[PDB]
Image (cartoon, rainbow, N blue to C red; front, side):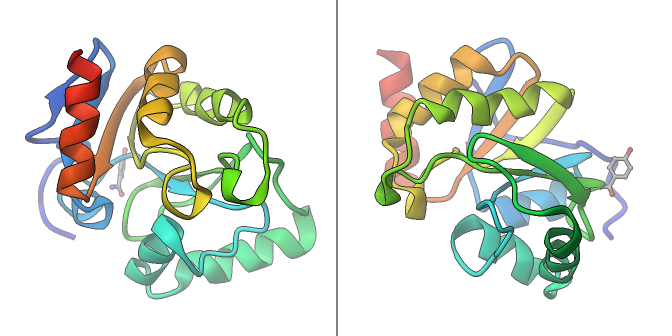
Length: 173
Ligand SMILES: NC(=O)c1ccc(O)cc1
C-alpha cells in the first residue's frame, strides 16, 4: 500500500463533534486513508454485485465476495439493521458490513437507526450514507439519522457533487 499512516482522513467538512463529510469516492478514500474500518452498504446475503458493495468488491479483485460467500454458507444471512465484521482486504483492516433498509423493496425505514447503531462499536469509520442509491432512502434523512445515532467518529464519503452540496446545505439550515 502507500506509505501513509493509517486513518489519515484529509479535507473533510466537520458537521458535528463526531460526523465529517467529503465529496469523494469511498474506494479512493480507502486507498488514501488506510482506515481501520470501512463500512460496506451490504445486503443480508452479502452479495456485492451492485451499489457501493460492488465498488468495494471490485477494488478487492473479488476477494470480498469470495470471503462473504464462504461466510454466508456456514453462518447464514444478516438481518436488516444488522452487521458483521469481515476482512478489510486491501481497503482497511476491517470491513463492517451494515444492512440498511431497502425502501425500494418495501423494508421499514425505521431500521436505519439500528443500521447506524452498528457504527458505535468502532471508534472511527470511513462510510457511505446508509440506505442511499439502490436502497432508495432519502439521503437528507439518512444524514440526520447518522448525526442523531452515531457517537463514534464517522467520515462520510459522498461521490455525487450535487448530492453532496444538497446534504451540506440541508445540514447547515
Ligand atoms: N489500513 C489498514 O490496513 C490498517 C492496519 C492497521 C490498523 O491498526 C488500522 C488499519
